[PDB]
Image 1 (cartoon, rainbow, N blue to C red):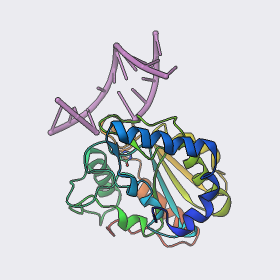
Image 2 (cartoon, rainbow, N blue to C red; image 1 turned 45 degrees about the vertical axis):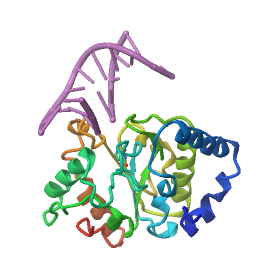
Image 3 (tube, rainbow, N blue to C red; image 1 turned 90 degrees about the horizontal axis):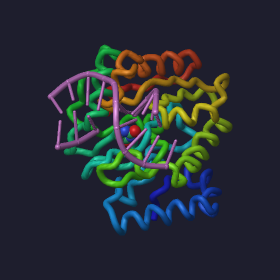
Image 4 (tube, rainbow, N blue to C red; image 1 turned 90 degrees about the vertical axis):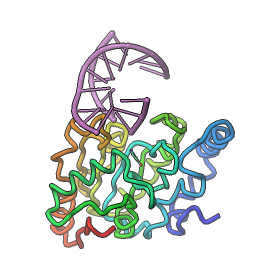
Length: 223
DNA sequence: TGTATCTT
DNA sequence: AAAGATAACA
Ligand SMILES: O=c1cc[nH]c(=O)[nH]1
């Protein structure tokens, strides 16, 4: 119980009774019986437990969870102490250090600090079979995360979406590019970071857009 | 050994 | 689809 934060469950509950969702949860359940799936069930929706849905100001959309033991916990790119930051996160910190002058490696990989500030740390696909990246794509997660993006698009204003990677970028078409700001770059994984993530300056750019629309910027060092 | 994106 | 090529790093 209580895997979903109250305000999130209230606005996404309409998906629960849909065939694709019932079949999606059915698939993940069958998978957990034969393989190790990440993150654990009680953490698949951690991204709804950090702030009220109406308080989201920035959305970071990744591809799918870390596929190693004890890494993924429901917030994209984040890992709970004492787990060391995986390759993707070390790259995010590397960019943050050159993008934000006051930013220095926090010495851990827990990104709850950002989420509590209204930064939704979402992935297009919310589960993954151990050691197999994007193994759970096209099973129904995409329509669910589409519902999340769609609600935010219609009920919020001036949000800043950071779509990292081709899969996250599939959601760009559902975002009113006039009402919200969409920043797109390569995924921070070592296998693609060199295609543009380094130098993208999305963190400083995100705050410029927020402050321009009179909103409090994100303190990226607040972790 | 191990962490995307484009092409056939 | 899904496998192969291409691709930084350590
Ligand atoms: O949560 C995560 C971690 C790495 N890469 C992603 O796309 N998401």
